[PDB]
Structure formats: structure tokens, C-alpha cells
Image (cartoon, rainbow over all chains, first blue to last red; front, side, top):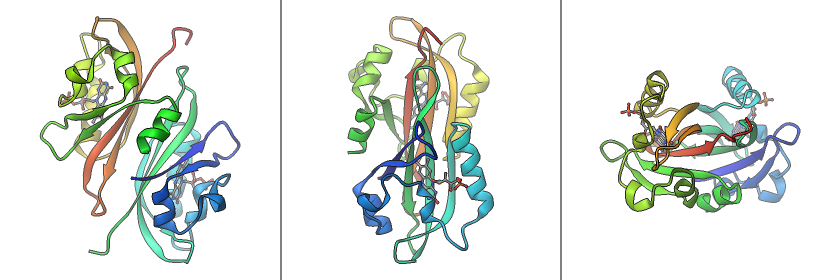
Amino acid sequence: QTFVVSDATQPHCPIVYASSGFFTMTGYSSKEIVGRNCRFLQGPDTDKNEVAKIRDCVKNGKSYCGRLLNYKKDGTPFWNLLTVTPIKDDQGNTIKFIGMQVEVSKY
Amino acid sequence: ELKTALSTLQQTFVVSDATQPHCPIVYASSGFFTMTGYSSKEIVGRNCRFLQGPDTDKNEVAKIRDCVKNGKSYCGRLLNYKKDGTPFWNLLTVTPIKDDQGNTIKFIGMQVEVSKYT
Ligand SMILES: Cc1cc2nc3c(=O)[nH]c(=O)nc-3n(C[C@H](O)[C@H](O)[C@H](O)COP(=O)(O)O)c2cc1C
Ligand SMILES: Cc1cc2nc3c(=O)[nH]c(=O)nc-3n(C[C@H](O)[C@H](O)[C@H](O)COP(=O)(O)O)c2cc1C
């Protein structure tokens, strides 16, 4: 599974871990993207309503599941089957999120 | 590796196989025994519904069911019970894992026992 971990205890939820498969999928290196928000995957044709749904989920520490258009480092458009799942502490605070990505195949 | 990232987060989790009838647990992390009192011998190959009991909110359970059945994500809090009967609040996520055709093939469930000071 390709995935990233973002730290919700830091402003704007920066990536703190990218799996080897994220690099394989997107072309971006772990040194290019750690410390950054995952929004860099979006581009001209990404559905902004779907982005707004993710933003709401993230802001409220709840789970997102959906499909959105993203772009690789080289500009290649792909369909990303995405989940973003809050990780909570024992007080119910959202401390991290895990985002899991699947590139929809051509067939 | 996903398992490792999770362990770095000290996160209790299970994985269920949506390709098998009734979505059985195929893997449970060591924290799942610690939290629930159930061994992997008691839990692997079963559905996680065994953690529910008399006062579990059946309307919340229904929301989980409807997410699982439709390959979507659940997030919520419900009353669960340890092997010894102890009730606990379980802050639960259930997240579909999909193949490259959009088929839900597994789920990952992440549990947090709510602290006594909350
Ligand atoms: C852990 C995690 C993983 C994410 N992965 C993606 C991604 O794969 N693709 C994407 O377009 N957005 C992804 N996002 C969503 C963006 O980072 C951001 O939350 C979204 O663009 C909405 O907020 P904004 O409108 O302020 O950008 C992810 C978010 C989190 C927290
Ligand atoms: C991966 C995964 C983890 C789950 N973890 C829990 C859990 O920790 N506690 C719980 O009560 N139910 C858990 N469930 C939900 C139940 O297994 C079941 O889906 C739910 O009770 C609704 O279906 P049912 O009405 O047929 O029982 C989990 C389900 C999945 C797929």
C-alpha cells in the first residue's frame, strides 16, 4: 500500500512520512515532500468541491474516502483513490492522519 | 512497513479481508491483545463484532455496517468489551483498502481506548 503520514499537531498538517510506494506512484522524493502539505498533487482539473470535502474532514478530525484527479511530478494526470484517516490520542484529539493512495489502472 | 509506521505511532489496529465472506480479521497488532485481552488465537479469522455487547449503540454499529458493506470509511466512538467483561470506549476508524480497479479488498481498523481522565 502506498501511504503518507501527516502531523496534525503542526500547522497545516505537513507530511512527516512518505512510503516507498508514494515515490514510485508520484515521482516526488521523500526529501522533496516531507514538511509539505499533500496538496501539491492537485492541479488545473482537480475537483475543488472534492478538495473542500477533504479540507472539512481534516479540519474536523474525521475520515475522508473518495476519488480525485492528481498529477505526478512530471505532469501526468492520474485518478487517485484516496483515503485520509485521523489518528487519535486517548483523549480523542487528532494527532496525525494517514493518507492511503491507489492509482486507478488504465484497464 | 505499513505495519512499522503504525507501530511507530503506537497504534493498535486490525486488518480484515473483504474478499472472504463476513470480512474476517486476518492480522491483529500486538496492542489489540493488550487493549482487548484477546489473543490472536481467539481473534484471527473472526469478525471484530465480538467486542460489542449489551449496551453498544446498535445505531452506531449500523453505521459501521453500512460503511463496510459499501467500501467506505467509518470514524466514530462506540462501547466495546474486553475479554474479561471490562467496558471501554473505543475510538474506532475503519478504512477500506482498494485495488487499482476501485474494488475494496481489505479494511484496516484502528482502535484507541479512551483514557479514564477524558
Ligand atoms: C495524510 C493526508 C494525505 C493526503 N493525501 C492527498 C493526496 O494523496 N492527494 C491530494 O490531492 N490531497 C491529499 N491530501 C489533502 C491535502 O493535503 C489537503 O488536506 C486538501 O488539499 C484540502 O485542504 P486545502 O484546501 O487547504 O488544500 C492529504 C491530506 C492528508 C492529511
Ligand atoms: C477492520 C475492521 C475493524 C473493526 N473493528 C471493530 C472494533 O474495534 N469494535 C467493534 O465493535 N467493531 C469493529 N468492526 C465492525 C464489526 O466488525 C462489524 O463490521 C459491525 O459490527 C457491523 O456489522 P454487523 O451488524 O454485521 O455486526 C470492525 C470492522 C472492520 C472491517
